[PDB]
Image: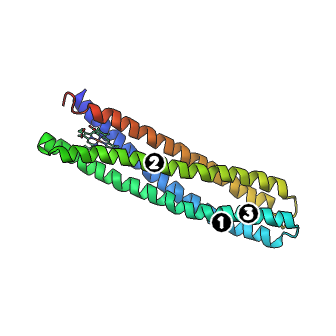
C-alpha cells in the first residue's frame, strides 16, 4: 500500500547502500591479495630453473598486472555507483517533498539515475567475472607445473589464489544481489505514485 510501499522503496535503497559499501571493501581486499600474490609469483619465478615453468609463471604474472589495472575500473564503477546512489537519495527525498510541484525534470532525473546505475553494476559485474575466470585458469596451471620443492611454493601460491577465488566468487554474488535490489527498486518505484 502507498505508505508501506514508500517505506519498502526507502528500505531497499538503504539495503543497497550498505551492499555497495560491502562490495567496495571486498574489492579493496581483493586488490591487496593481487599485490601480495604478485610478490609470491616473482619469488617462485626467480628460483624457477625449468624454462617452461618459468614461462608459465611469467604469463600468470602478466595476467596479474592486467588484473591490477582492471581493479582501477572496478573501483571507479563502484565509486560512480555510490555517487549515483547519493543523487538517487537526494532526488528521491525532493520528489516526496515537492511532488509534481517539483516539475518533470526531477522525475526524469531519478529515472535516468536508476537507468545509469544499473549499467554501472553490469559493467562492474562483467569486469569481476573476467578476472575470476582467469584465476580459475591460474590454479590449473599452478597445480600442473609445480611440484613439491621448497622454491616452487606450490602451497603458498595456490593458497593465495584459492583465497582470491573465494573472494571473487563472493564479489560476483554480492553484485548479483545488487542488480536484484535495483530491479526491485524499479518495481516498487513505478508503483509509488500510482495511488500516491
Ligand atoms: C538505489 C536507490 C534507488 C533506485 C535505484 C531508485 C529507482 C527508482 C525508480 C526506477 C523509480 C521509478 C521511476 C519512474 O517513475 O520512471 C523510482 C521512483 C521513486 N523513487 Fe526511487 N530509487 C532509489 C531510491 C530512492 C530514495 C532513497 C527515495 C527517497 C525518498 C526515492 C524516491 C522515489 C520516489 C518518490 C519515486 C516516485 C516518483 C517517480 O517516479 O519519480 N527513491 N525510484
Residue drawn at point x = 35 percent, y = 56 percent: 83
Q: Are marks 3 and 1 in contact (CB under 8 Å)?
A: no
The residue that label 3 is drawn on is: 59
Instruction: Residue 113 in the image: state x and y as whole percent.
Output: 32, 48
Position of 25 with respect to 44 (left or right) is left
- The 10 Å Cα crowd at callout 1, few under 14, some 14 to 19, many 20 or more, is few
Pick whichever, 190 or 93, lies toward us: 190
Q: Earlier in the sequence, mark 1 or mark 2?
A: 1
Ligand 1 shows up in the quarter that is top left
Q: CA distance from mark 1 to mark 2?
A: 27 Å
Q: Judge left or right: residue 45 versus residue 14.
A: right
Which residue, given by chain and number where applicable, does mark 2 sit on? Answer: 121
Indicate which disc residue 80 carries: none
How many residues crowd mark 3 within 10 Å: few (<14), some (14–19), many (20+)?
A: few
The secondary structure type at the circle numbered 3 is helix
Q: Earlier in the sequence, mark 3 or mark 2?
A: 3
Q: Please tell me whether residue 125 is drawn above or below residue 47 in the rendered image.
A: above
Q: Are marks 1 and 2 in contact (CB under 8 Å)?
A: no
- Residue picked out by circle 1: 36
For label 2, the crowd category at 10 Å Cα-Cα, with few meaning under 14, some 14 to 19 and many 20 or more, is many
- Residue 176 percent across, percent down from the top left: 50, 41
Judged from the image, the secondary structure of the residue bearing numbered disc 2 is: helix
Measured in 3D between alpha carbons, the distance from the residue under mark 3 to the one under mark 2, in whole angstroms, is: 29 Å
Amino acid at each position: 500500500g502507498s505508505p508501506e510501499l514508500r517505506q519498502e522503496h526507502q528500505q531497499l535503497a538503504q539495503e543497497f547502500q550498505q551492499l555497495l559499501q560491502e562490495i567496495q571493501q571486498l574489492g579493496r581486499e581483493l586488490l591487496k591479495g593481487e599485490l601480495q600474490g604478485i610478490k609470491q609469483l616473482r619469488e617462485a619465478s626467480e628460483k624457477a630453473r625449468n624454462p617452461e615453468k618459468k614461462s608459465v609463471l611469467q604469463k600468470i604474472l602478466e595476467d596479474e598486472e592486467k588484473h591490477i589495472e582492471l581493479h582501477e575500473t572496478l573501483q571507479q564503477t563502484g565509486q560512480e555507483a555510490q555517487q549515483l546512489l547519493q543523487e538517487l537519495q537526494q532526488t528521491g527525498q525532493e520528489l516526496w517533498q515537492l511532488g509534481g510541484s517539483g516539475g518533470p525534470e526531477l522525475r526524469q532525473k531519478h529515472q535516468q539515475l536508476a537507468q545509469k546505475i544499473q549499467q554501472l553494476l553490469q559493467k562492474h559485474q562483467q569486469l569481476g567475472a573476467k578476472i575470476l575466470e582467469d584465476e580459475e585458469k591460474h590454479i590449473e596451471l599452478l597445480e600442473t607445473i609445480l611440484g613439491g620443492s621448497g622454491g616452487d611454493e606450490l602451497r603458498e601460491l595456490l593458497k593465495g589464489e584459492l583465497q582470491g577465488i573465494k573472494q571473487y566468487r563472493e564479489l560476483q554474488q554480492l553484485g548479483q544481489k545488487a542488480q536484484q535490489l535495483v530491479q526491485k527498486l524499479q518495481q516498487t518505484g513505478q508503483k509509488l505514485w500510482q495511488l500516491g
